[PDB]
Image (cartoon, coloured by chain):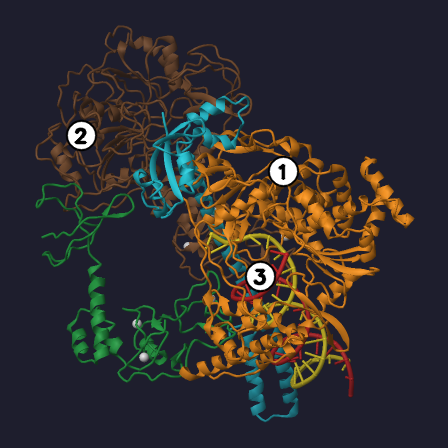
Chain colours: A orange, B cyan, C green, D brown, E red, F yellow
Amino acid sequence: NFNVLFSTVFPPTSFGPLVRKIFVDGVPFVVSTGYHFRELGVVHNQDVNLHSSRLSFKELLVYAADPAMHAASGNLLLDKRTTCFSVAALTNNVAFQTVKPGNFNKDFYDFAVSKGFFKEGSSVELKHFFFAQDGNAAISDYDYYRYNLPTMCDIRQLLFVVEVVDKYFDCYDGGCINANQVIVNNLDKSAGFPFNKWGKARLYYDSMSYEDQDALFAYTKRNVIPTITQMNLKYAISAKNRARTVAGVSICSTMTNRQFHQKLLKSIAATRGATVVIGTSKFYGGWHNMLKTVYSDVENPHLMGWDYPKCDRAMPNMLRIMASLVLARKHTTCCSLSHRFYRLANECAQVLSEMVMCGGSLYVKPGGTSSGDATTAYANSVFNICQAVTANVNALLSTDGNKIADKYVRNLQHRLYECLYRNRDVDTDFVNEFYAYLRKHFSMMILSDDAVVCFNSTYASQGLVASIKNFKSVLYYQNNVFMSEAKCWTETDLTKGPHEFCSQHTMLVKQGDDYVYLPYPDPSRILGAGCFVDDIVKTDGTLMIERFVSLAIDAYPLTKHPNQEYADVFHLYLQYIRKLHDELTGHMLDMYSVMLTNDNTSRYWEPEFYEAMYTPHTVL
Amino acid sequence: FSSLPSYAAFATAQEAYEQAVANGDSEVVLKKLKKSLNVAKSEFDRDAAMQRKLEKMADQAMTQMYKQARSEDKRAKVTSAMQTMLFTMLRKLDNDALNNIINNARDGCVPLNIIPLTTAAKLMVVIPDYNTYKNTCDGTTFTYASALWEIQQVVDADSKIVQLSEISMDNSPNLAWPLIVTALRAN
Amino acid sequence: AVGACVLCNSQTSLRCGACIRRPFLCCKCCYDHVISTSHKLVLSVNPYVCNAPGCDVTDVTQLYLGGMSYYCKSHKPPISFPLCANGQVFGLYKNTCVGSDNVTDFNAIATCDWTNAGDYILANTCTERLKLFAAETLKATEETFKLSYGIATVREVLSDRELHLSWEVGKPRPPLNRNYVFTGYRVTKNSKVQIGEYTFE
Amino acid sequence: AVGACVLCNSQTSLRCGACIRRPFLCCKCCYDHVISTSHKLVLSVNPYVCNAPGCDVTDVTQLYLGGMSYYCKSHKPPISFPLCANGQVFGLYKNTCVGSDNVTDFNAIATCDWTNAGDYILANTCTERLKLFAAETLKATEETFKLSYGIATVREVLSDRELHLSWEVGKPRPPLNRNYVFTGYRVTKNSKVQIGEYTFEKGAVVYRGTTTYKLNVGDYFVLTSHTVMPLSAPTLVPQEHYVRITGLYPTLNISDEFSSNVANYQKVGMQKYSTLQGPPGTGKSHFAIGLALYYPSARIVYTACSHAAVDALCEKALKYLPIDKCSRIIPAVECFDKFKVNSTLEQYVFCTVNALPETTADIVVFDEISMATNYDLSVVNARLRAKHYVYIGDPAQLPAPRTLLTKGTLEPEYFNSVCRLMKTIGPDMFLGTCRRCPAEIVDTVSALVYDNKLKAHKDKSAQCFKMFYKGVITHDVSSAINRPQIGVVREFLTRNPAWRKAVFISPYNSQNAVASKILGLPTQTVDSSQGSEYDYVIFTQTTETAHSCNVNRFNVAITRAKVGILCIMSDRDLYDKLQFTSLEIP
RNA sequence: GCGGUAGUAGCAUGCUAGGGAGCAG
RNA sequence: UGACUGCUCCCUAGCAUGCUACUACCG
Ligand SMILES: [Zn+2]
Ligand SMILES: [Zn+2]
Ligand SMILES: [Zn+2]
Ligand SMILES: [Zn+2]
Ligand SMILES: [Zn+2]
Ligand SMILES: [Zn+2]
Ligand SMILES: [Zn+2]
């Protein structure tokens, strides 16, 4: 906290990797043997050898991921398009990347029009398209890191909020695992910066044996390895016309972050009935179970949801450090005290402030999160819980204590002030008491910066529980953003669920004998997915009929909506599926002579196959 | 599947038993036929099953070892490629200015952000518009980072040569404006 | 992919693996192409070959169509039906095929080295499209037997119209007049560079 | 892990584990080699050893395959499968083998521990890849033998031409002269530091090296054993006499360096190789120099076998050929750096086979064939792939330092493949012109091996002397001494005034060191001392045993001196063959 | 007379592996 | 040029378990 304030005086060219000259068989290299953080000060590597013989495979991998050689063997660059610090240009040309439009499925559009759709004055219309971008879009989108400013925190209050958050994250287990227990899916994805010139992640997960991976992972508990992050543009459907960009982290960072965090990440995504709902599905009655869990037994229930403007471009560094420290608290037996600090330093040097490669040039990332590391959603959930806790603390500590009728709450406020500003060490009994109070009067359900809260209403009116205004104030003074209350909702009737959670609305329908909650999407999104595609994937439905089956699975609960076009969407999808099947069979029987059969294929255009996906009895 | 060790015995016993049956002998020879053929087929059963299990096991082993060999070959070639890339990028370090600024350090360590700033030979500037251009690289030589640079070439967003005589205020709206200026360190 | 075999009037996706122009032959037509001569390899939308890693079978007469793939004889998962069976080869248009009465058109003129007079004799005893196949195969054989001789080059130069010339490794030299234009290319280090048009007599 | 087997050239994945060089063996070849020989270890992509925990068996005929690992009789699962069966080991490409019948000779090559003459007989009597494998394993065993020696513990130095140096405990004194190079590396605190390329004189330690270092503490003198790389090219390429002179350009004029050099070119321009069959000082030097300017537009390579024999390699090249046309290749030991190092484009490169800048040519010259093995021929054929080349050297010279053989001497037919290639079918070239030499060597080596194709060019005044003295031999250490040399040098310089400035051939280098300590004569090496001979030399007794005197060590020693060649009859020499003047000692 | 065992065929259930596709943060 | 997670549908291959069936051996 003090280093953050003091680092704003010193010049910005004295931060980052520290390099020196080493000799390998009489030839000189330039490698990084330390780091200078704005928050953590000066860090020196522990195992550095100047004179050495011919190097091995993992040394080649480490030296090929360091930005030192790439920056030192490049040209100077002065870029006036952005205000962020610039390092070097790797080539003699600047690359401009564009985004192409979508492909039009005319047959589906004609079929939909021939059934009374897209008429004037209708309540269902297309507002999801593929937007195109011009040459200078990647740099324009990268220039949004100017909203990240150095922020000092109230340390005596953060040191209590972190205890409450750790109480929230208490029902799991974690630790370190060996290289043979790591689970990777889709090994056919990109590998990072230097490495995408020779293969995908399969090449590097096959060429490296198990003890090589173990030695590489054990190397990062005594040294710091800075890497390079590549920025890519997305090609997907959306409702707004701004460019979207994701970050591609290097393989040397992901390979070790998996071994560090995967056990805890898998343990979190396997628990039901907790605050974090990552891993729970919405089919087979999952949505109803989540909604019933979040309602708990609150006394005067209302519902509330909020929004984070520029969530990843504006999150201060201190909260990211806090999230990493909270996640790394499960290593009390497998790791020492220096190993944990060096792991934290490696994480900070790789995914918090490092060189990014936009276009064909190297830039310096000021701060924030790089969406695309191995621990994105869980860290976002920790950050969301931290913000909710500090909002509750600020709401309770800023109330006239002479007007609180209940004496228990008055004593709680007195003890809260004493534990914040008059106590130096942790007091577990009051932490447990405050955690119980929060869980009784303020219930949460969190999924990576999306949240729904069921709170006591009279307590919030009297000021003993956080409100929207408290969230606005906390965001203003701790996140450097303004949160307009036009993107937040409030629901005073519990028979209708949250107004929006994970882009889905909620309706209470009668199925069987009882009443359950079902989610339904926006009809415009489903129709836009039907009509606008990437080529070959559609514009010929017979080649892929399984797209429309999934799209009709997503659009089933629209048949219980009081509005009439909403069910017509599902019926139109069923008729299109039947038409595509008939087209395929006849269109194949005609020129060729192969005769097709309709055995157990009619199930796809009858509603009973889709009705079974929302009825509790987990058949897969 | 036809020349198994027990096949000869099984077939010979079957042929002899069926010849005895075709001889129309008493029921005792028929009972002996049935017992002998039953035990013969029973003993042929495992000899026909175990061999088929073993062949599939051997085939799986062969496939796994082949894929291991392919993985090793790929590892060797990627190692060669990485070594070549490193030794190729080594040859542009300008080993006199770099040595001159390394020796001035009190322990050999220097920040990475000041190596291109003090040892690079070429500079690239990207200019949004003309107002920014006339404040940064006006003329033929300009000063930046406490050094003197002289212009060598100017191209546009389409990578076509542009002469400085036509970068003016009147002619500004006729150029693909993300201009890139290349200069060399003077003296 | 989908071309046309016309003597049997059969759209096809098959083609002979080892032949002149990758010619197109229907199921029965590829069959009597592969039994009247020796052409034991075919090409379809995908090539027929065992798909287990490390396996190698050029022949098609013993491959099987397995689990959305092809497997073989020496390395045999035989839960399938054979590819080559019942007077036909497996592919599309396996039902709408006719066959050929004159079995040895390809077996006669596509099986010799395309230099005897019999080639042209049969080409004139053909139809319009059959003789089109003939003419295209004559152009193909012209080029494919022209690409079997040397490349002239001047390494030290002399006065124009009187130079020195070394040629190639072991290959023979074609006829001598200006029939063959010596219009090659120049190499600086990896690329091709403006040379012009020449002729050596 | 995948390649061709040394006999069938078929694809395999099996490596024999009981052969020091780990050759690639075919599956049928693997079975034949493992059955008829106690070579019971086979390596694959994974080793063929029992993986049962706590177990240790390294056979191949004993293991059973089960599950995914390999198991033995004591741990075979119910689902087991023997690896060694059907006379064919289990490995990749098992169905695409052909086998071979040349397994007995391959077994003999593998099993031969290199003891007797038959070792080299069968080394030179086999097919090509077996020749390559035999040469590789011969150099491997000799380098292992010489690395099985101690480290020279040194902590101080007296002065120049003096040294105190100690070997290890249980290790004997290594061989003496530069034939076994002494190149060591000391340590200061953390790594190794340079010492110098040296050689020792006696046991007083004079320095016959070419540098002087601040030698004292922590010094480690060692005969550096080097890892041997595998061969690529065969020992020789079969020649075919051309009709076109491709690339070769006989100039309009005649660069008349030598007269018969025109015929030289005439028959070396068509066949894929040749050889300069040169008696000492008989055009063995500058015929290539004449070829340099008669064929000036031809890429010409020059090489030898040792860094010592570069005299004629380097002198006349700069002396008469143009300055720029020459080029120098030297690792950086101490040798002639007269031409330009670090230059890839040139037409006349002069070096040794130690290290060259990888390129191909069309003309090469290669010196010192007598002490050249098939390994050196293969490496020069691999590094340089030319159109024609000449191997300078003569069978009437010394063998390579093949200290491995002790029973039978290695004769001309056993030098290398080429050295008998020109012995059976005849030499590519045969000269008969001695540049500067009386007819003593003419008579001697023409009656012995030259077959009298060269005759008297300079007159025979019979000033050379050979006496009736015999001598007495005594062994002490791996070098011996001679009392009828300690007394005999004086007894032979008693009154004859002509051989006081003669050169001392050294069958025993320690004896030459003692002679230098007592009376004083220059030390003259035997093997690597051709062309360094002066005008006047003494052939001394120095030995009677089978160390040096059967035929081919004195064929060049008789040519060291020109007029006054004192070659006394020492032992069972060629006494009753010629006429020689004699003076009887008092 | 009943049970056990050994192969063979059809059917059902849950995992692992491979491929194609959909949604969400 | 194509990031990190979560859930779901379809197709094929293998393994394990269970149900039924057909022969044969044994008591
Ligand atoms: Zn740990
Ligand atoms: Zn054909
Ligand atoms: Zn046909
Ligand atoms: Zn196969
Ligand atoms: Zn062996
Ligand atoms: Zn073999
Ligand atoms: Zn064992």
Q: Is residue C46 left or right of residue A82?
A: left
Q: Position of residue A288 (x, y in %)?
A: 74, 67
Residue placed most toward the observer, A532 or A193: A532
Q: Position of residue A93 (x, y in %)?
A: 39, 43
Query: What secondary structure is marked by label 1?
Result: loop
- The 10 Å Cα crowd at callout 3, few under 14, some 14 to 19, many 20 or more, is many
The amino acid at mark 3 is Phe
- Per the image, the residue denoted by label 1 is A150
Quarter of the N terminus of chain A within the rendering = top right
- Per the image, the residue denoted by label 2 is D287
Q: Chain of mark 1?
A: A
Q: Chain of mark 2?
A: D
Q: Position of residue B57 (x, y in %)?
A: 57, 64
The amino acid at mark 2 is Phe
Query: What secondary structure is marked by label 3?
Result: strand
- Per the image, the residue denoted by label 3 is D81
Q: Chain of mark 3?
A: D
